[PDB]
Length: 358
Image 1 (tube, one colour):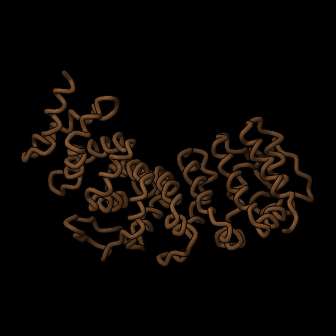
Image 2 (tube, one colour):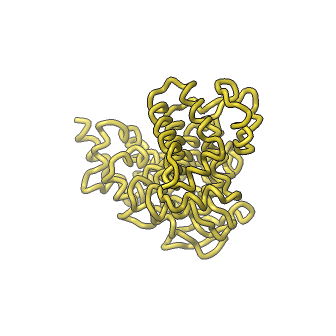
Image 3 (cartoon, one colour):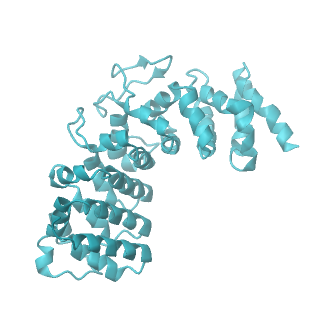
């Protein structure tokens, strides 16, 4: 019935005629969500391969065809086995994808960021850290016409550097009218789970001489972009996996890590901290606006509390946190937010900060 119709239809994705393909994918895009999507897994994932070729085709890959192909791939990238095909079957696609996001004339940038964030679960995503290009202008990389970079915006030839630039400077449609790059937050979140990924975020990069994690910190207070807050929260937590890195990161004043972990758990109104404690708080936590509130999403608060808890691993870290009135902030969070997961974490932090010197 429908299964029989779709099996025949999917094969037209590799018809030699462009007109035929354009029609085939137009009809198929609707069936990529829900039980009918099994059809895209025929011939050991041949439809996925054909769709990838259609997207990358420089002549016949129109705006609509790219949008429909990516929309399919976003839906199908829930399956782990499909993500494998997207990354490993053709190594060109990942290069194509990241470079087309940083193309500020690409109208399908955001939908592509969603695809990228889904692919970041598979550890084959680490390839992004090595994807560079020879020149700033137009270039042919393994038969791919890469668009010329905006030299005014992107100073790096590294892909990961340029994606950071898009996220940090492109929020609220500031680089492109078509996109705000929000879902790159989830890309950074999932890639920083891996060792080599964490290492990008906590080390100086040449192109702008800064430690990337610092550039994301400001977005913990971005209360009109829930996706950004969630991803950045996880990236910070994942960046702190190594105890021995904690002293360096807390004390680097150019990074200025701690205040942006604390701000989302701080409130002006529902919080009584005496003035002795308040004088030890970081500058950014003192004289808070009257309307200053905690992040309303408990999942995000818990993530920040997990970061604080990580920092409590080492004695030097515990001393740093104590000296910045982290205890009173945690106490008042506990007092004023009924959530039970938040509460459990608050006690675990206090248990740690109660320790002396080993």
